[PDB]
Image 1 (cartoon, rainbow, N blue to C red):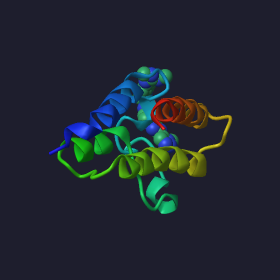
Image 2: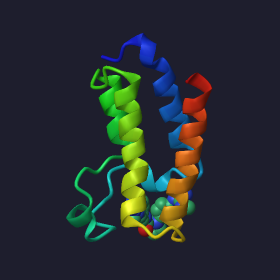
Image 3: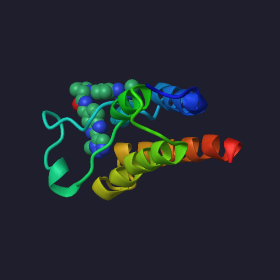
Length: 105
Ligand SMILES: C/N=C(\NC)Nc1ccc(N2CCC[C@H]2C(=O)NCc2ccc3[nH]c(-c4cnnn4C)nc3c2)cc1
């Protein structure tokens, strides 16, 4: 399971999930609601997947955790127009994450 040294990542992820702009990213992009997603996006990622991976030991390092966080935002930029509601949410969440990551590095 998660090593205590990564508790700061657990907290960042919890705070991301609670953010007003997090709604598009809480769970895997749902084919029932969004069509053609995996056609374009080779490596989907979302906050619930990260939460489970972190909590069960699937991130050995903060760098691996951060790479999945950035993948959420990179996928969002790939799939969505910048002026769409989801596109805007991705930019908000990237800024929020990078701010929190800056406090530590
Ligand atoms: C400001 N709204 C909220 N604040 C808390 N909550 C909220 C949630 C759902 C709904 N509705 C209302 C009708 C049904 C549901 C709906 O359409 N859900 C679609 C949905 C859900 C997640 C997504 N994630 C990406 C995505 C990610 N990356 N690319 N995309 C295209 N699309 C998504 C589409 C109404 C309000």
